Amino acid sequence: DRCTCTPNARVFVAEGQVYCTRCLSARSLLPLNLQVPELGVLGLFYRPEEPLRWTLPRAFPTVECSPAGACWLSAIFPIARMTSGNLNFQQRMVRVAAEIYRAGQLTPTVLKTLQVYERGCRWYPIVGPVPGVGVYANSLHVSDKPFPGATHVLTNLPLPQRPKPEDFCPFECAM
Amino acid sequence: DRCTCTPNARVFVAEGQVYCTRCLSARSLLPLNLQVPELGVLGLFYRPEEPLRWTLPRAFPTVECSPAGACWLSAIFPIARMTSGNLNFQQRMVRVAAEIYRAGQLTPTVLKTLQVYERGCRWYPIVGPVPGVGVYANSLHVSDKPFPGATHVLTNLPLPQRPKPEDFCPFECAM
Ligand SMILES: [Zn+2]
Ligand SMILES: [Zn+2]
Ligand SMILES: [Zn+2]
Ligand SMILES: [Zn+2]
């Protein structure tokens, strides 16, 4: 039982799995006939409706950048979950993906547009394990799980450490 | 940087880590001088204030029961997160742990007391990967992650499958 939406339905990455932004079901590999070579790893699952507006170089996942080239695909779910409630999530997931996909990267400006801070998320200097969902990051990459190099974690959890002021963001352009 | 609360502060298990119910920081092993042998694995981190009211047999984690004997320690965080908001979580975490610890097991009655269903959680027959936090289970055990044997997943996520009526619960006594 996999996702059966039109292949132009956006995708996000949680832990290992590629999931559909529309139905939240695991996404299988695209038929290669539909695959969009110009979109690296993303094109292996996502086939947009029209142009691209930006491209993705096919590559291997680095110990810190995964999916290689568009690690922000990994921040879509955590930002949406920490930024919505029970009867509000779908709408949120859809708006968060659209924003990020459009920008083709994660940036302080895209986080402001998404009101991540006003909704309860705070960055924290990683000093140990953090339970639940979150966005781990450094000055160039982000992930939904900890990784070698990550220096900060974005969470809505009332942590013991001291939150970073709202003007702070570990990166300028996480890709 | 670990937890530095009084050792009588309750504990919960998320993924691998043992975390403190009070400060949400990782919990180190108890000095063995404080360790409470009568509380199996739990006693290796948690030292109550007075009696026990129930005991825990020391053992090895089974492919389906972990922590061995009190796998419900793994359901504390997911139930609390899916059942609270941003400015409400701590209170929720504290009430959820106390309830479960008292009952010394997870049961349909303890889930009703915690109003898991009225707050948005629904059980679903596992048919594929599910992103985010959740409680995986079968008729005898539960976990915060999928495991060989699990047949159902409790989530507040608006999944595509069809939710189980509110009278349904995969188990009668998950320990
Ligand atoms: Zn879909
Ligand atoms: Zn990257
Ligand atoms: Zn503590
Ligand atoms: Zn068990």
Image: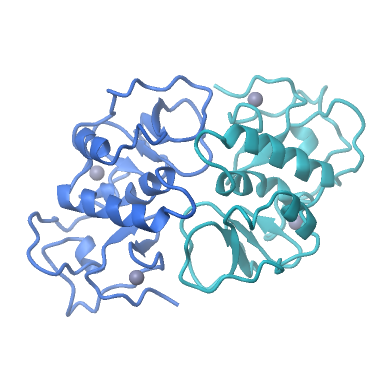
Chain colours: A cyan, B blue
Q: Is residue B39 above or below residue A96?
A: below
Residue B125 showing in the rendered view: yes
Q: Quadrant of the N terminus of chain A?
A: top right
Q: Nearer the viewer, residue B151 or A144?
A: A144
Q: Is residue A146 above or below residue B144?
A: below
Residue found at x 71% / y 45%:
A73
Q: Residue B20: x percent and y percent?
A: 34, 65
Residue found at x 37% / y 73%:
B3
Q: Nearer the viewer, residue B3 or B116?
A: B116
Q: Residue B174: x percent and y percent?
A: 22, 39
Indicate left or right for B16 with B99 as reference.
Answer: right
Residue found at x 32% / y 24%:
B166
Q: Quadrant of the C terminus of chain A?
A: bottom right
Indicate left or right for B163 with B169 as reference.
Answer: right
- How many numbered marks, from 0 up? 0
In which of the image's four quarters is ligand 2 placed?
bottom right
Indicate left or right for B114 with B23 as reference.
Answer: left
Q: Residue A4: x percent and y percent?
A: 65, 19
Residue found at x 57% / y 70%:
A163
Q: Residue B56: x percent and y percent?
A: 14, 56
Residue A19 showing in the rendered view: no
Q: Quadrant of residue A166?
A: bottom right
Q: Is residue A52 above or below residue A135?
A: above
